[PDB]
Each structure stands twice: as structure tokens, then as C-alpha cells.
Picture 1 (cartoon, rainbow, N blue to C red):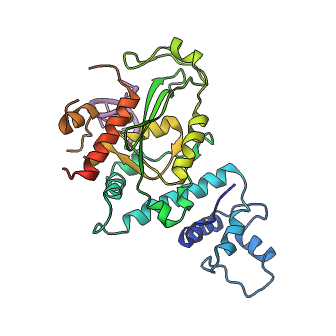
Picture 2: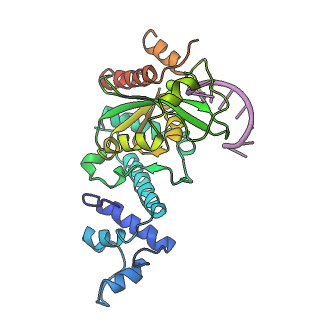
Picture 3: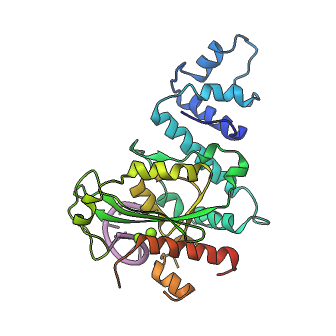
Length: 288
RNA sequence: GCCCAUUAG
Ligand SMILES: [Mg+2]
Ligand SMILES: [Mg+2]
């Protein structure tokens, strides 16, 4: 179900418009189908700038299936990053400075585009909180370790999330639904390690991250999209370390090395903490 | 923009 309580009207309007546009069917089908069965008056205008969310939300809650809901969440997130761009620099806050940069940077539009949604995907809904939540400034750095799977589809074996204070938040071993051909060790554990530690899955870590995301947490990371992509999470507020600070994108070891002293196997929790540490680095102390 | 390379892993 869809939670439109404190959503902004602008967003709400736009969503309805899209629905109208794609002519989609809900419990009651169309927006004007709906607006006619639900409004007796001929008088009623169709421009969902007719005022109370309630006029909007009700329709919006007509739509039950996953596809339409991912659709609407998606649009609302996009809409968010859009309002994000349309506000001037002048008193914007260092964390939002950062997200500004890493969605403004021209690479973003292509890299962080995830559709089509497998409908194993989780789409964040922070696109429907109120503004004060949307502009929330709290960070948590993700990172993954993946191994190429039989499918040629990459897969999730180790995930780490880390908080603003480098306190470690989700460190885990995942064993993928589909088997795997190449474990890419050095930078990995071995399959023997995981199967026993079978417990964690991807839907589990979506479950786990969802309350952070809906409270509007800024994810932070380095080439964070490869991560999101294996995690099957599409959430607008992001900070990519590569993108922020020559077309070529940097590598983490050189940024730290560049930022502060740091060929050995990779560690997603050190990774996450390092990413986080750079983000904080800019936020408190100004850099370039 | 696909391949490439950097990033990732
Ligand atoms: Mg990374
Ligand atoms: Mg890593």
C-alpha cells in the first residue's frame, strides 16, 4: 500500500497527471472514471490542482499492484531530485551540497538509471514524505562485495552499512539464490564461508534499510550504483564519492591517500567507513 | 551512449 499522508501537493498532482496520461486502471480504473463515480457534480474540474490531497489520495489509493506503485514512487523520487536542483546554492547545506553535486554531475543520469524494475526491486518512497523529511541531512554509507554469478549477472555476497560516526550497522554475508561461477578472490571470502551463513538475503536487507530510507537517509558510497544495483534498491538521495571530488573517475584508495593516509583484498565495511569518512571530511572541513 | 578504458568488484 501507499502512504500519502504528508506528501506534498505538487508531487501528488504530478502523480495523478501521469496516471491520467498513461490511462491506468485501478480499483475504479481511470482518473475521470474515478472522478465521475466518486463525484456526483458535473461541476468538478479535472485538473488535479483541485485542492485537497484527499481529493488526490483517494484516487491514488485505487492502485494496488506493484508495477503502478513502483511507477509512482519512481516519479516522486525523480520529482524530488528535480526540486533539489531548482533551489539555489546560497544557503544550501553541506550534505545537500554533496547530493546536489552527485546528481548534477552528467554521469549520473545514465549510471543511476535502474529501470526496468524486476519487481524484485525496491523503490524508496521518500518521494512522498513532507519536505522537512525530504531535506533530511543524515547519512549512512553502504558498500558491497559481489561475485560474478553463473548468470553473468553479478551477485551479492557481503554487505556493510556504516553510520555517520563509523559505528557499524549491517555487516553480513549473503548467499545468492542462483549459484556462482567466479568468486573473484582475492577480494572475497570463499563459497564454503557463505552457504553455512545462508541466513541473509537481499529482500532482508531491503527490509532492513527501508525505515532509514523513508526517514530520508542520504546514502553515501563510491560508485554507489553498482551497490544499489546488486541490492535492488532505487533511492534518490545519494552521495557518490567518485562523482563529487578530467572525465575519469577516481579510485577509493587514492582519494583517501589523497585525503589522508590509507593491492589487498577488499572490505566493504572498511570501504563504507572510508567513503563515509570522506563525506564527513568535506562536510565539517571544507575541501577541493 | 553499445563495446573500451577509469570506477567497481
Ligand atoms: Mg563501493
Ligand atoms: Mg567493497
